Length: 273
Ligand SMILES: NC(=O)c1ccc[n+]([C@@H]2O[C@H](COP(=O)([O-])OP(=O)(O)OC[C@H]3O[C@@H](n4cnc5c(N)ncnc54)[C@H](OP(=O)(O)O)[C@@H]3O)[C@@H](O)[C@H]2O)c1
Image (cartoon, rainbow, N blue to C red; front, side, top):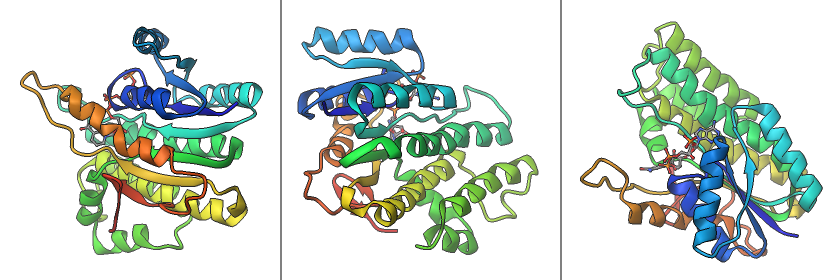
C-alpha cells in the first residue's frame, strides 16, 4: 500500500537512498533510472543483498516518462508517499561544450525537469507524504555570487513559481546572449540550477500550505554534504552512503512533524541564507 520513489537511482547517492529506504521505509521502494539496463542491474544488486525494490523507468527530461510513472503510481498504489528528486547533472571540462549549452542543459535537468517531476507528482502525493529535492550547498555560494538585485529576487518570500521559472529562463538566455555577468549572474550553471531547486522547494511548500495544509505534506531541499574524492578520482563509497543520511531523514519525518517545511537542510540542520 505505501510507496517511496527515488530518481537517478542506479548509481551514486540515489542508489544509496534507494537502499536505505528499502531498509527503513514501511512500504515498497521504486528505484527508477533513465537507462533501464543500469536500473535493472542496480535492482539486482540490491536483490543480491536480500532487498526487494521495484523498478520503473524514468527520464526526468521526458514528460511522457514522468507521466507514465505518474500513471503507474496511481494505478498500483493510488498515489505516492515519498518522492526523492535526486537526478542531476554537472558537466566538467572533459565534456567540452560552449557555456550557453552547458547552462541550458544543466538547468534543463536540474531545474526544469525537477520542477516537472514536482508538478506531475505532487497531486498524487498522499496525506503525510514527503518530497525531498536534492540540492547542493553550492546553491549558497551561487546566491552570494549573484548581484544584490538578484539576491533580493531569489530571497523574497513572495516569489512565485512563475517568477522563478522566468528567472531560470533568463539565466539561460543571458548566457546565449553573452551578457550573464553584466546581468548579475554567477559563473556556475550547476550552482544557479541548485539555487533554483532550493527556491522551488520553498515555493512548493507555500503552495502546499495554501491549497492542502491538512494533508501535512513536507517538501524540503537537501544538501547530501561534501563527498570526498578517492585516489582514483571517484567519490569515496563510504561518503556516498553517508550522503543518503539527510535525504532519508527528510523522507521519513514522522507524520506529526510540521517542520522542516520548505527548508534547505544539511546534516539534518536548516541552512539559513
Ligand atoms: N556527490 C557529491 O559530491 C554531491 C554533493 C552535493 C550534492 N550532490 C547532489 O546529489 C545528487 C546525486 O549526486 P551523485 O553524485 O550521486 O550523482 P551521479 O553519481 O552523477 O548520478 C546521477 C544520477 O542521476 C541520473 N540522471 C541524470 N540525468 C537524468 C535524467 N534526465 N533522468 C533520470 N536520471 C538522470 C544519472 O543517470 P545515468 O547513470 O544514466 O547518468 C544517475 O543515476 C545530485 O542531485 C547531486 O547534484 C552530490
